[PDB]
Amino acid sequence: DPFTMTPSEDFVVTDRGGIVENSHRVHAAVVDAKGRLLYALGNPTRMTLARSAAKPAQALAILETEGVAGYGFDDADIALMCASHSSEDRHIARTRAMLSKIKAEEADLRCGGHPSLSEMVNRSWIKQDFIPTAVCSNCSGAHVGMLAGARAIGAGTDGYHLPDHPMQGRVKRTVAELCDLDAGDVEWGTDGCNLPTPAFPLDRLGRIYAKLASAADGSDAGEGQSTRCAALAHIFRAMARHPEMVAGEGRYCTMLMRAFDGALVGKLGADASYAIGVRASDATRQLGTDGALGISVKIEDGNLEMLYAVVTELLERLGIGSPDVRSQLASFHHPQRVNTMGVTTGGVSFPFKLRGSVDDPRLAAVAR
Amino acid sequence: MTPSEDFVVTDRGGIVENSHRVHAAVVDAKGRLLYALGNPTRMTLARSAAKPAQALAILETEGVAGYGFDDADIALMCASHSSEDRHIARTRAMLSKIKAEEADLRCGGHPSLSEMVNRSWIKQDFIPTAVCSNCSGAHVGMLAGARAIGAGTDGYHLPDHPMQGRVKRTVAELCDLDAGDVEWGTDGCNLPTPAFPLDRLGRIYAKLASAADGSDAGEGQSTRCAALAHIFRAMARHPEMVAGEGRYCTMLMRAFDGALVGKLGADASYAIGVRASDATRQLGTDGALGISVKIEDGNLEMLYAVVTELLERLGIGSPDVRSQLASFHHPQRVNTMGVTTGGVSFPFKLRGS
Ligand SMILES: NC(=O)C[C@H](N)C(=O)O
Ligand SMILES: NC(=O)C[C@H](N)C(=O)O
């Protein structure tokens, strides 16, 4: 019944010859530069671990640490602070160059190695029986930035990653401030790279990224800016200018940001969250806001292949980009379902319904 | 009768990370529903959890007995194996028994179901071929069937071939369904693959274990019940052929040492046939039973956790026997620095009849 559809029915589904294989619940928020909710799927306020989708907030805390500017991190270094990189040789090399800029060593890192986020890099490592180490961590840039901050303020470096350290006090405050939340409304766990990692309502992830894009707009327009807004504009510009530092070759975030050529930034969170900050455009105005826009998505069960398909579908439905811009992402939008003998056996479909405009006022939209 | 909201939930520091909807059916030897999670009649692609039904169609084909397939061979017919060297070797030995060659196979190679095997392949620049297919044993069996009735081999995998007619008929008969109540797609190994209500998958495996109980007891058995008993015995005796080293199905079957068989379906279905036992009697049935599970979003890690939790709640096996599956039951959640970051919980409740 098309007239009784509900947020609990917002799914992405794979089929085999039209027979349902898997289904995945979708949550999404689309917000303006103040965080006002414009459009949604599922539960737009779902309490959600942002994971590395919070890295730009961490980068901001680093860049606002007094004395960090003296180290001379450049835009590519800052993009690496914002990264979940593929551990390509260029990422490892930039991590080492950033350590050198602060006169630290790999032994000062408190993150550990892991298999690469890139299948092609992992393949090279397997052939050499290479064991990744701290300097290969997908989060190495943020860890180097945290060490830089710890050094700059005269804190110890030994536990820069622990919650009682002033660098982590700074991160925690910065995250809550960007979300416009009280500290008690942000919860904290520990991430795979051994840093505190925040959870907050999903819409507030979109709010962070709307603020990034909004700051980019104000900077480009030559408006006088607070030190925080200037830093948020710098982070936006760094990510958009060096999107390969943020992820790597063949990675969704890199292909997405290259396709849009400065119009937006986007960032993956592990276990299938995604955040996009969209600069003001004809598209955002058609969506009904006079400023920048933020988008946040979570696939409830954590499937990344479905995440990229859903994010690309949502961009198409919001009219963000051109068919030509978004077709650089076609392999993520409609994932290949081809068996071992070259036969297409099924596909992906998007039975979810954006809400925010039409329905009978007696239709309840219960966030679920 | 509305399906419960049954989930397995992962957390990070007590904060919800992912959740996964669980469907499960526990059925007696006639397929009567005894316990359930979620929607026990969910229309579900059985994928390779249907392999024992396909092995039954092979074994019932006229003349297949003359090739001399043994119990390990039949286990391979029932398998989604890890493409270990010993699985490839047995595939080749089975092809030799029917005087066929790898070129006759109509399945294709793929990355191994074992990450460890696949890393060894990557290290050696190895490109998997037809003989490496996790379904190679079933394909050799279907080739053997085609040859045995003189059907000719080029399209043994196609729906219009009498071998697939036999498979299609056998699946519906084991489910006790009309042909129209089974739907058909195409699998990764390029065979027809069935979808039917999830409880009927449990019914297949209850019939497998019931047949083993009746064979053991010396009962008069149909040729079909005799063959189902043989399939059960083949899987339990050669569980390494069904999957491989470190695989859940192999470790599950070794742990239970003949009390049950279990089989994975791709995209996170699972089926178990349990021979009659003190545990099954405690659950309120006088015969064998079947268990079928589907994780709605297709997550395999969560599948194995849920299946092992279900076995604990059902009392199937001793605590000592189930502890061999501890690493599947509560998957590790330890970060790159050795710190435990989270866990898995099972807020579902089995509902009974
Ligand atoms: N990259 C992410 O989203 C978080 C991951 N667990 C990490 O810290 O490496
Ligand atoms: N192994 C399974 O469950 C089916 C798999 N896609 C295959 O045909 O190889």
Image: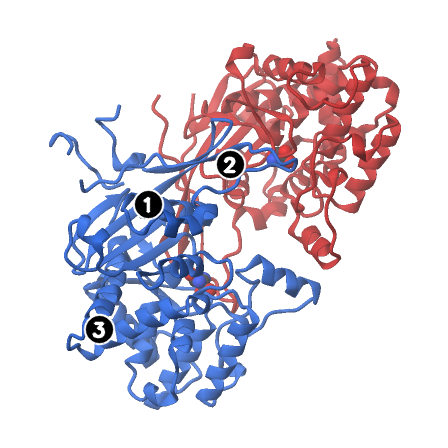
Chain colours: A blue, B red
Crowd class of label 2 (few under 14; some 14 to 19; many from 20; radius 10 Å): many
Is residue B28 or residue A58 the one in the foreground? A58
Q: Amino acid at mark 1?
A: Glu
Q: Which mark is residue A316?
A: 1
Q: In the rendered image, which quarter is residue A3 located in?
A: top left
Q: CA distance from mark 2 to mark 3?
A: 57 Å
Q: Which mark is residue B310?
A: 2
Q: Quick check: can you spot residue B233?
A: yes
Judge whether A262 appears above or below B23 on screen. below
Percent x, y of residue B7:
40, 39
Q: Residue at x 28, y 80 (%)?
A: A64
Q: Are dots 2 and 3 in contact, CB under 8 Å?
A: no
Q: CA distance from mark 2 to mark 1?
A: 42 Å
Q: CA distance from mark 1 to mark 3?
A: 28 Å
Q: Quick check: can you spot residue B288?
A: no
* N-term-proximal mark, 1 vs 3: 3
Tell me the mark number nearer the camera, choosing from 2 and 1: 1
Judge whether A282 appears above or below A142 on screen. above
Percent x, y of residue B96:
88, 31
Which residue is tagged 3? A219
**SS at circle 3:** helix
State left or right for residue B38 relative to residue B324.
left
Q: Amino acid at mark 3?
A: Ser
